Image (tube, rainbow, N blue to C red; front, side):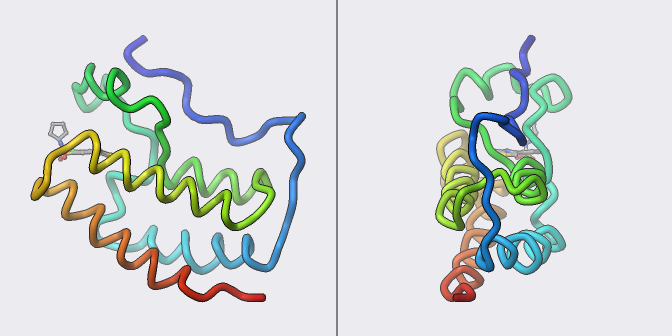
Length: 125
Ligand SMILES: O=c1[nH]c(-c2ccc(Cl)c(S(=O)(=O)NC3CCCC3)c2)cs1
């Protein structure tokens, strides 16, 4: 298929964890970003069949999206906040890689990244 399987949202041989920071990343960071007017392209894995982008997964080898991140947080999939933050950063970076400076989609990612950084600047202790 043109679409690989989406990233795992559970893994039984990976240990789980819950922390105040991870709770915050779900309740505040993810759930607030989700509502932004520019969040929609990032709420699910890129569907190359739907969007007609047979090139997407030829270019992006570590795909990530907020739908996956949300499910991971709900699963307690992550060990710590930094691991989750890395997924957000991978999502943003993928967008910059797959596209071009100034593209509408890149403008969207740039705005979301700024808001994301604002919110993770300070996490609970
Ligand atoms: O690098 C990424 N692009 C996208 C994405 C998702 C949906 C849509 Cl419509 C778009 S887009 O920038 O408006 N390009 C559309 C024009 C043809 C394919 C989709 C990008 C999510 S991550």
